[PDB]
Image 1 (spheres, one colour):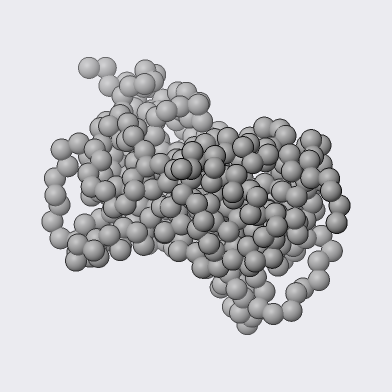
Image 2 (cartoon, each protein chain N blue to C red):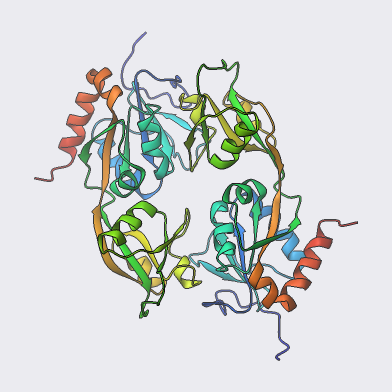
Length: 227
Length: 227
């Protein structure tokens, strides 16, 4: 009837296989820093997603639905065109791989550095180094950069915990300030590369839904005044 | 040879490389159902770990510290002897396929069935089926059992979401009641195996710290209404 792109009724206005627009967001501190930029494109959630039973959220904009995903899955969904576009840390994107996707924007949010780390005042142990990390490939590639080989240990949860209980000799995680690190008696060591949230678009979706995407991108671009 | 074993100091003792005992627990519905049985063995936390900034919890026993891990990491820690023993879903244990570990106890808690699932009135697709799943190997092995080969899509988070947004043809997840499934218009389909939380012990840890372990195991065994 009205088709006002202001969709205020929450608990409603959510069709499935949306051939409007499907946005995949990394839950947690990325989301917090993401929404401000979405805010300044007239795109906002309509309940606390943390306190919501929904898996698919409708938004203030009627042509846009949101997924709150584990960071690792965001590129997975967009790669496959489940999601038309998404917001993922460069760390995740680089580790996961960039396939059927365009990386359109450095959003300059959830900015941090992929770093090695150890127990404060630690002595490099002797054999193959044991490295606890979510970012296996990136760690494997980074020590390959230094012509070293390492034993990797894949972790999904707290990387902070590993070295305290003597799981890793070292860890590789993303580091904002490394205050949390110091507070748990750890130290950031070697910067592997800089990291920030990046906007990605399924290549197909990008060709197909150009009408919807252009304006949103434009507004997101402007929301970042990094000039 | 000291005699004190009890400890009510919370935010105390704990510390690093405990050559007492290190217990790795899964963080979800498992934990809730786990602690009662630990209670029975005189092993209990002394604060809400959910509301604690602490990473390593001390317990009622001075010889026992606790880690609350993502289910996926528990076998990782015990495999490596970071943790002396742990509690993980058979699903995770089978998928991870840990090495240096004894599976000593079916705790018959967080019981459920690893199942395939589809959209309500799903259409058998054509060609090689896309399966969204956390449990890649177990899915790969299970369709290998039926002599079919499938395209797997690894997920870390909610597998429930995939088919709604048309990611998978089907999904493989654990199904305790599968109410959540029916709620967003999905169906349980088949049964790949039955699943429950299991107690696991690093083989080395078992040899070395047998004096501490035997008592706990014994009491945990009995706490499952053993006959």
